[PDB]
Image (tube, rainbow, N blue to C red):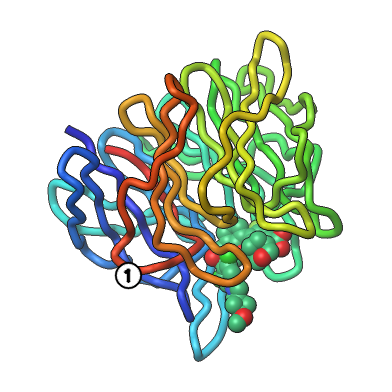
Amino acid sequence: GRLIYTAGGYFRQSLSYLEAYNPSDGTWLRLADLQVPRSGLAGCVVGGLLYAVGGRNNSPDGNTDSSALDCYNPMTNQWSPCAPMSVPRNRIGVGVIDGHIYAVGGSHGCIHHNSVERYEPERDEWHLVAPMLTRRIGVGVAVLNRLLYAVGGFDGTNRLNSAECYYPERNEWRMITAMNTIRSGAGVCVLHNCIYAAGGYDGQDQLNSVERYDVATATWTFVAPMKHRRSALGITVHQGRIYVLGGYDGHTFLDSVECYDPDTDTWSEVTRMTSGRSGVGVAVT
Ligand SMILES: COC1CC2(C1)CN(c1cc(Cl)c(C(=O)N3COc4c(cccc4-c4cc(N5[C@@H]6CC[C@H]5COC6)c(C(=O)O)cc4F)C3)c(Cl)c1)C2
């Protein structure tokens, strides 16, 4: 059995919540809080351990971008600090290849990173890899066919519909087919050999649209839109289905959790988070 973990987020200030949802019975476990509250972080899992990467602590006493990497063990209910990244990265994207964590883009104040770095849990060390062709904050990250994809975001001037791919053996990036829609702060994941980009902001409107990248045809196709338009949503895959958690729609910090079934091409509202929040990091283990 596996759970959907949600770490951090934002509602009035950055949050430290760590909760786990069980899609089988609809329950939520309240787990050990993060040591530092963070929103705009990303989550990932390597060897059954959950990692909270980057983000920012927006508090009444100040706003600080995070270069932190923290590791949570579900067996011990404890968070442990790991080696920090070279730079703080708020609104970061993360992907895992062969048990190695890639921290992609994100911001540190007014700096919009195009830099990318890779963490080895086996050595507790980070190292920079080739930088992206585009600076991207609010970027979605997908791992497919041992390639790392960086989708959408904001380059410091424009919100982006562009996407690019990293080749680990060659240590290089190339631009791929751009999405139909500009999406900054979308939820990006991989399901059944396809990349999905759900929601996000196009520069004018919060989106409920969802599009899917097919590798063989190099095309983005729209699938069923979500019930609730949202940006800065958590996203993950559990048992062949996509789950989107929270986010912000221009008026509300959503507690909605929707689930996409690819066989029927339908979204259904399956539960609510214990409190409405945006900018969470999510992972399954
Ligand atoms: C009472 O007024 C207050 C309430 C207020 C203003 C504090 N409000 C807040 C405060 C916060 Cl700390 C957040 C939040 O969770 N963040 C900050 O943005 C992001 C987070 C994570 C991923 C992407 C974005 C992002 C979010 C963006 N924004 C888009 C889509 C969401 C966000 C705002 O709407 C436009 C953009 C962008 O502008 O392109 C780029 C991104 F990387 C984390 C949100 Cl979502 C709203 C909203």
Residue 248 position within the rendered picture, expressed as x and y whole percent measured from the top left: 55, 63
Q: Is residue 88 visible?
A: no
For the point 62% across and 27% down, the residue is 212
Mark 1, Cα crowd under 10 Å, few <14 / some 14-19 / many 20+, is few
Q: Amino acid at mark 1?
A: Gln
Query: From the image, which quarter does the N terminus lie in?
Result: top left
Which residue is rendered at x = 51% and y = 61% of the image? 279
Q: Secondary structure at mark 1?
A: loop
Q: Position of residue 38 (x, y in %)?
A: 45, 67
Q: Is residue 128 above or below residue 201?
A: above
Q: Residue at x 81, y 59 (%)?
A: 156
Q: Which residue is mark 1?
A: 35
Please state if 57 lies on the left or on the right of 25 as rendered: right
Q: Would you place residue 54 above or below residue 266 in this image?
A: below
Please indicate, yes or no, whether residue 260 appears anywhere in the rendered image: yes
Residue 70, x across and y down, in percent: 37, 56
Residue 237, image quadrant? top left
Q: Position of residue 164 (x, y in %)?
A: 73, 31
Q: Quadrant of the C terminus?
A: top left
